[PDB]
Length: 38
Length: 85
Image 1 (cartoon, chains in turn yellow, red):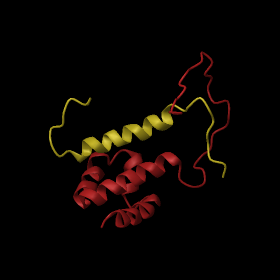
Image 2 (cartoon, one colour):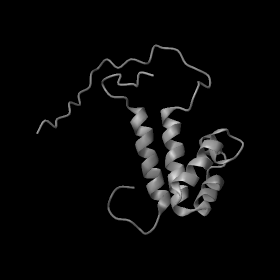
Image 3 (tube, chains in turn brown, cyan):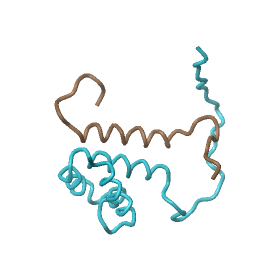
């Protein structure tokens, strides 16, 4: 976790970080209903 | 210079007083991104990386698309082939 440093080539680490973003993205919706019309 | 964001909250944040669906039409924006993300990484590191995920998350239905048992597998496998080069 965090941003101290990296331990080496760990794709799994970056994958879980990308996953966190998508999860959180849909977890907290913004203050406005900005959805796509069709 | 017009860059500014307004990020405030309110004490009134009730639950969604709307209905629910049971397996709606087309893939959700969430899963869409998850499949792409996965398909991009597997295409960048090779099948070995993919197979590892298929082991560690075998009991997580969200990774079941990696198996041909899901229709999403078709979309996913076709995406890997496009992300590889």
